[PDB]
Structure formats: structure tokens, C-alpha cells
Image (tube, rainbow over all chains, first blue to last red; front, side, top):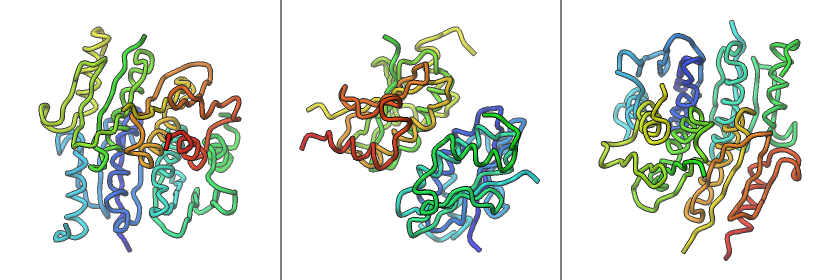
Length: 84
Length: 85
Length: 84
Length: 82
């Protein structure tokens, strides 16, 4: 096992760019802790991210798109809450 | 149900950049046909790409890193052979 | 003599990823009007974007980093005011 | 006093921003404090020509396609003025 983050994004909305960006922000700072970050096309304004099935971000629910710093923290807390 | 691709890459070699680029190339061309494209951290200068377990590229096997068009043709023949690019 | 957009970014801060991301977003939706988008490494902790010398974003001033939505907008006002 | 700048001209409708942006990052993540800037210049007619202070270090036609990371990194390195 190892954590697997998945970013689901609306293709037509043209959110691949940012999906790919956030995927690299993660794989950069957590290159040794993550098993894999997946990019998953979707439709109708979908933009959701989860870690091992746990939602750590969702467009309408969190007000838009995450700051790299925030998503990092939420992935951090998800893996080891007490790891700086 | 849709086919998935996995680009396993050596992080220390600093190949995330490539892996990401190729994942994006693939996703913009097969947005309606790819289940998902994964970026997988690894080591020892590994750079292998799978399309549902089936290898379509392996650094030492194909002499380096694939080209945009070539990887597209491979994924294509794999999922949609009758499709033109 | 088309408009230039430069994004000055702090390299040690590992902000190249977001600078290249925002670059691509601009080149994406303004592919036919921008002469080019430049990425300029700054030795200091900066992140400011100018359009033909006119600053359109500054980390400290504008509160952080911009959302693609906002940036696209400010650049729109700066060059082609009549767009959606 | 005037650090070298790289320009990557690419055909837009060919959908080459990606491979041009990718290369741009490849250079900046390797030559952070050695390059003044790396510019992405939209173009047409399947053009792809990279310059380093005017000095073309690659052009799709002449060079036969698109550069490797290794290569362009080496051709940019060969221009740093020691």
C-alpha cells in the first residue's frame, strides 16, 4: 500500500492544465510518500480530489480550486497528521 | 471500464516533468476514451508506460523517451486502431 | 509588435510550476493575441506579472497567487477589453 | 549584466504549447540562475524554432522534429559564456 491521489476534472471546461499542475505540485513535495497521482477526465464542471478515496477538495464545496499550499497540507494531514 | 495508462518514472532522475507532459499530451488527445492517466513515482532510472498492463514504452526497451506522436499512435492502436490522428 | 506577458517567479521557492501553469493558461485562451509569455527567474521571493510593463499582479499587493480566472480577466482588460 | 534569454517559437493550432512549455520548464529547472528568461512565442505553419539570444539552437526542419531534454539542455549549456 501507499497513498494514491486522484484528481477528477471536467475536460470540456479546459481544466486539464490546472489538474496536471496540481498533480506535479503534489508529486514534487511528496515524491517519496505517494504511490501515484491520477488524472481522471470527467464532465459538467467536475473538479474533485481525493486521497485513498477521501475527498480533500471539491469545487462547489470548497469554493473553487485549491491553493497548492492548501492541497499539500490536506494531503499531508491525510498521510501523517504529525509530519511537517 | 475505459482503458487506463500509467507512466511510471524515476523521481530522482527528475523525470516528473516529462511524465507530466506526456500524460497531458495523452489526455488532450484521448479525453473521451481514457479512463485515467496515472503518474507513478519510482527509482533507478525507470521510465515505463503501460496502457492497461500492456507495455507501450520502456526506456531501455525503446531507447529513451517516446515522442509525442509515437506514444499517441501506440495508445491509439491499443484502444482505437481505426482512428486517424 | 504584440503584447508580452512576463511572470517573474522565485526559483528557490519552487514556484516555477505555477508560473509555467499560469503561462500555459494565458497562451491557451489568448493564443491569437499575445506575442509571447515569458518566465523570468527572480532571486528574491517574488511572483509578479506584467503585461507590456504594466503590472497586473503582485503576490504581496494582490494577496498571494492568482486564480487562472482572475488573471485571464486582468489580461483581457489590458489588451482585448471586448471579450468573454 | 544581461543574462541569456531563450525563446521557444511554436505553432499554436498544431497544439504545441504543451511540448514547448514542457521544454521551457526543463530549461528553467536546470538553469535557474543562468537564464534571464525563457519565452513562449505563439506562431503558425508548424514552426518550432528555439533561439538563445538570437542564436538558433534548434529548428524542427533543420534538426528533424523536436529536441530531447538531454540535447537542448546541452545546447543551452554550450551558450552560457563562462
